[PDB]
Image (tube, coloured by chain):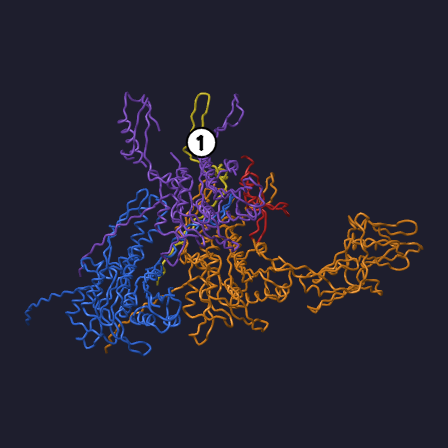
Chain colours: A blue, B purple, C orange, D yellow, E red
Amino acid sequence: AVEPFPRRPITRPHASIEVDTSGIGGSAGSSEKVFCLIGQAEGGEPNTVYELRNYSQAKRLFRSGELLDAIELAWGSNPNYTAGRILAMRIEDAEPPATWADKLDKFAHEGGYYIVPLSSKQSVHAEVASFVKERSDAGEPMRAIVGGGFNESKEQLFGRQASLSNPRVSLVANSGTFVMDDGRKNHVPAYMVAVALGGLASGLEIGESITFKPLRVSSLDQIYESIDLDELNENGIISIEFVRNRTNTFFRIVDDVTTFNDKSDPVKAEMAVGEANDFLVSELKVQLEDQFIGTRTINTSASIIKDFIQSYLGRKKRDNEIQDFPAEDVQVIVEGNEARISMTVYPIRSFKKISVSLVYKQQTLQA
Amino acid sequence: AVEPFPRRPITRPHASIEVDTSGIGGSAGSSEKVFCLIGQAEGGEPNTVYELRNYSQAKRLFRSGELLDAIELAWGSNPNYTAGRILAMRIEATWADKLDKFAHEGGYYIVPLSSKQSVHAEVASFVKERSDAGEPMRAIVGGGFNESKEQLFGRQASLSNPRVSLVANSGTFVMDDGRKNHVPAYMVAVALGGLASGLEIGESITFKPLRVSSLDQIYESIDLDELNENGIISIEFVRNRTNTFFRIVDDVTTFNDKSDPVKAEMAVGEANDFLVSEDQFIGTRTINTSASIIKDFIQSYLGRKKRDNFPAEDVQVIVEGNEARISMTVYPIRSFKKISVSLVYKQQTLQA
Amino acid sequence: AVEPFPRRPITRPHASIEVDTSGIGGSAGSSEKVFCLIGQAEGGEPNTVYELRNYSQAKRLFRSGELLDAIELAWGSNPNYTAGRILAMRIEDAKPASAEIGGLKITSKIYGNVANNIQVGLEKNTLSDSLRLRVIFQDDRFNEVYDNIGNIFTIKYKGEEANATFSVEHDEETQKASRLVLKVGDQEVKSYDLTGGAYDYTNAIITDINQLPDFEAKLSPFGDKNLESSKLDKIENANIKDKAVYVKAVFGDLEKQTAYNGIVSFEQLNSPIKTIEPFELTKLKGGTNGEPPATWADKLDKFAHEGGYYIVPLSSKQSVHAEVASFVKERSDAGEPMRAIVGGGFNESKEQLFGRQASLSNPRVSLVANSGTFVMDDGRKNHVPAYMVAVALGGLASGLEIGESITFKPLRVSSLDQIYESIDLDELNENGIISIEFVRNRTNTFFRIVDDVTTFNDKSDPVKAEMAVGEANDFLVSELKVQLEDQFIGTRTINTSASIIKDFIQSYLGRKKRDNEIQDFPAEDVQVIVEGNEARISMTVYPIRSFKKISVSLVYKQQTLQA
Amino acid sequence: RKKRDNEIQDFPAEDVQVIVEGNEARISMTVYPIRSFKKISVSLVYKQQTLQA
Amino acid sequence: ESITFKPLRVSSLDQIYESIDLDELNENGIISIEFVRNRTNTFFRIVDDVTTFN
């Protein structure tokens, strides 16, 4: 803005100052991913959302229940990365709830992106799928991560992935044994592994894949063979590989394939680039809206909007949230009611194939 | 005019000086958009239009009444803008005879502090009677404390006029005494009129914030679209951020028509009310003419001028009855309501 | 100006000088961040703003009330900075104590219930033919006596004639002395007009009369007494032949000698006028405080055009906070920038602090969360509501330089009622509430001010979010307005005027850079256009900013060592 | 001389034009008069600079 | 040379006009004397040299 000093005008001879702050006013940084959990628990009032920052704070707001273990796994499984905020909600009817759709809505305008329901029921999975679709269509992009029960055959997994083929749901096959800060080792259903994967994905930078990131678990109940893992990957089911040929044995997340059945478009198939797309569109929308709508269509606006877009995309390039963009494709056309804007973006892709061609050749040494 | 010195004429030998002052005259600029209010107060002498310049003077003349709360909101919604003059009158039923008193007080926006539809119709009639004269005006009005969408539509249809806007929402303002003052929607209309008076000539209140504490009703996107399309102003509670705030959705007018911006959108109507508009060669210099050679001549002229300093597709010529009207198109400054972004994902081969 | 010598011109052949002083005049330095408090206390005139420079002066005006404790914290909190002036005002209305006796009004110069302990008493000294006045007041251990009161000068007649008398004429219109008359025998020998001309002072009459052979005159034995001759007391036919008659003024001598008395002022009852007569000692009565005012708005108005920048009201009431918020706003908008700092009660929950911050969002107000204890110069350890901590923060902010932030500075506080975890200080800061951090990781443990955030939530604009930047802006634009006003308005548009203004602006910004009140100015961006009746000036300024983040990226690298 | 005393601001020399006819001198001139300052408007643009070492 | 903002030397003024009062009188072409109060030094300015012409 620009402001007069004094604010009240003066008629008689005087000096007055007009001051412009746009050059020092800040700007919104890169948005933050926040992780959402819905859980059976003991503790605080049900059906309200708590922002949580510390395990101690969580262990005061909640006690002795699977939600608190889920929060523990969510922070503990990503040691290398900054521990983000978590949004958590106990659920009980004011007895077991018949439906969660009535409660999921209380997340709707929270600043939250990844959802995990702490239950195995396919109906709950469908409910959260519908909710994530709803909010995305409303313009609040979200994703869900989903998992089975304690132990499931490939047949059951394929059945579930049939029941939910969706670009905003991911299914986690493996269930395993974790080790807890309480000095406890517990067998858990696969959705707790999905909690771990959501913690890692929400910790990672925007547009960074969970594929081939390590996972920390005491054991897995199902150790899938190479053909088994290829089968599940073809079906768009996330699987955990036990690395055995290395001297050190550890568990990899094999891939970040969504449950969606068509692999031809990566923006729908792969979580990372879909997330990058979601954040890029959301930030473009909200920033252009608050920047320009209602402003006067002064003759130079065709410059100013191009300069704004080029600045924004330069900032996106700086953070490695896009690969590159052509500056000259940023083009603006102004008509009396409307700004019409064109841009090209090169998005950032994770490496998923490396092909080495090795040519043996002779050289004649001589002396 | 040119001044003779001496003023008296003289015929004996003398010198006289003629002074052309006209190269220095000024103050030719516009009026400011003075704001106008009518409503209940204590203390002030009824049916007298007072100029007010600060809230202390207001509390000195008016007291203990809704007009002073209105003056407060009228300067409280726009703290980051010039706090300009306000015109206000205590009214102690027909209102036209009172509104007549504003007729030669140079103020552009008026709000009646009443929800009664007869009052609003009177005010619209007054705005018409003034604006068809040489002194344009506009009005803003609002409903009661809570009115349904169908009531608001019925009101807008009954009050459908290109110089009146209806505001739907009502809410609570924190006053400078700290009171949580719950107010009917016409005080929100006062707040919007204050903002619109503070903004520059042909700035627009769309997507400006409203410094209000809460709203009686929160409308979802479909209801905001419904009210906007019906030409009713509505306030959005912006929920997509931790920094939540209230936003004026649009500056629509109770006359809604897609075919004319000037009657649909308040800011362009104001621009038209305030915009300003800006060489001859005679046929005796030529044996005969036509609109074709008139057009080509004036194109050659303005080509030379624009080279020193216009598109042939944008000048029209009509010749009639020894007279030629040459009509240029001109482009005024509007304000963006739509932004359309086409985002194309390419991919690129890197090499090293 | 260019000054002519002589000022009056000459039209003979002559020489004349024209001196230009404009090269040596200097200009005013950076404005004082005078600090303002409004407070209850005993003593001092109600609704009066006092400039204060010493705590001794304050404790003489204000008698141990909470205002004096606030002034104590305001100076005492950070002694490594030069002490500022303070503006102080007493909130409650308070009547002085008074009495009526002996023909006189007696009135206290102090105000409030303490004044009812004043007592005064008046008696005849029958040896000096004088009054004697006692004044005693216990609360200060004050006791003073004034004696030989009333006698001012004397006349003796030393002629051989039997009859000689002194007389003073009334002026029944005014009760003043109209004339002095000396009679010898059946006639006046000499007489003087007392209420005008050369004899309007007693000393001049004493000087003149001593010239006459038969008469001689002298001042009173005690003290040093002179009066406007109008105040001479009515005396008739006093036989100056037998003995040296003392001429008297009673009320005039009371007035004159008590002029420097700080405890009691005297006025005379009426027209007929009552004779001054001795009376048994009486206490003063009716001095009292009233009820505390329901609104402070009309009292905060008294600080208007008192050139002080930070205000703290000594109250926890939200209504008072909204009042001072409005006052700060209106003074700012009228071109007298201000800020207020505000605090809660004794210990109030975090929900209540968010309540206050939501109810009072304004970029010119700040709210202080913590409440705690201080150790006073009296040696008390006292427990104080958070607005007294806000007083301490205001004293610091007024002690720091212009734009020097209170962010991350030590607070000389003994303890806090609430010590907040990291996350609670995070949340209070995010909501724009000032808090005090107990730094435990050091061996020396001490209290830091967490941040100087204002209560205005939107962090987007630093001139709104941060006190230091808003302060620097306010002083910049204020000193620009006032100096361009006094330097150039009404001056002629000489053909060079734009260059002169450009030089003046560059000089000013050079000073602001020198003093570290801006980071820099690109001097090429200073542009001035003069067009007819006005100048338009444009300048670029890089504002001074406190550090509030440091990021270190630390890269390990191997090194190969060989020998 | 008027310019020297700051009684006018300036004048264009080339606008001083004289036409002579048998009875009459006809004289043209332009003057820029001198005005007191009655308005001063300051526009202040805050801007950032990146210091580095 | 204008008398506007030149100093004036007077012991006191009977009517001290407020800022709005001075603006009103200046609009009406009436010369008014302003009591400068915000400066440490208090003095009287001649506000303007407006003639009575409308």
State the image coordinates of residue B150 (x, y, percent, origin top left). Answer: 39, 45
Residue at (43%, 68%) from the top-left corner? C424
Which residue position is annotated with label 1? D29
- Residue C487 seen in the figure: no
In the picture, the quarter occupied by the C terminus of chain A is: bottom left
SS class of the residue under badge 1? Answer: loop
| Residue B198 in which image quadrant | top left
Above/below status of B72 relative to A196: above
| Residue A157 in which image quadrant | bottom left
Depth order, front residue of B350/C40? C40
| Residue A53 in which image quadrant | bottom left
Above/below status of A251 relative to B127: below
State the image coordinates of residue B350 (x, y, percent, origin top left). Answer: 19, 59
Residue at (47%, 72%) from the top-left corner? C446
Depth order, front residue of B323/C255? B323
Depth order, front residue of C276/C199? C276
For badge 1, the amino acid type reads Met
State the image coordinates of residue C167 (x, y, percent, origin top left). Answer: 86, 53
Q: Chain of mark 1?
A: D
Depth order, front residue of B345/A300? B345
State the image coordinates of residue C491 (x, y, percent, origin top left). Answer: 51, 44
- Residue B166 seen in the figure: yes
Mark 1 neighbour density, 10 Å: few (under 14) some (14–19) many (20 or more): few
